[PDB]
Length: 199
Ligand SMILES: Nc1nc2c(ncn2[C@@H]2O[C@H](COP(=O)(O)OP(=O)(O)O)[C@@H](O)[C@H]2O)c(=O)[nH]1
Ligand SMILES: [Mg+2]
Image (cartoon, rainbow, N blue to C red):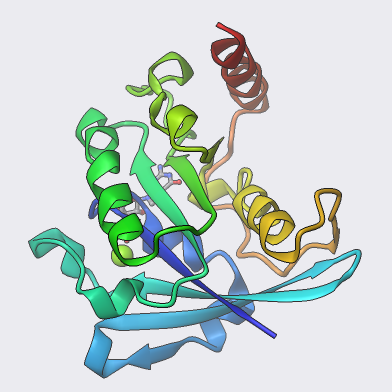
């Protein structure tokens, strides 16, 4: 049985494109009229059994202001997203985290910089600092290529289940990649995060 996960971040960062990679979750999503939300059931399969994240994706209302308390309430974990091609979206991460922690004081949170498939990257590893003092794990992701798609969910499942060595035994069916994540760029970016972390 299951965990509410709230996916937040500026409009246009790729939240909806990311949750939709999980094809069953997209097929089985439940639209909640009263709340302005689609709830996608993303089941994943660990070496210890299944875990279900019910991922709350907005219906775009973040473009007009903050989300209502009912969106965040009873969340057990979260993903904050920004877009590595837009510094302003990164600049706004602290405010999203504040809103989230205001309603859900002690939950595990992953920070994700999306669209790392785009060659002209504006927010690089050296610049991504917010997660350090706040105890968040960070990953680069590219929703459109499934790059690192399972990373945030695996880190969350380890935190939520209380098993640091949990692994996924099989991947969910994901929408086939719509863009190629350049494998060279992926390897440099993962190492660049490791370097920034040691600096
Ligand atoms: N290149 C690229 N474009 C993306 C990615 N994710 C989303 N997009 C594009 O970014 C725009 C906003 O995506 P959307 O999922 O609607 O963002 P949301 O408003 O945060 O829900 C759309 O044009 C997407 O196709 C990605 O990983 N790579
Ligand atoms: Mg959206």
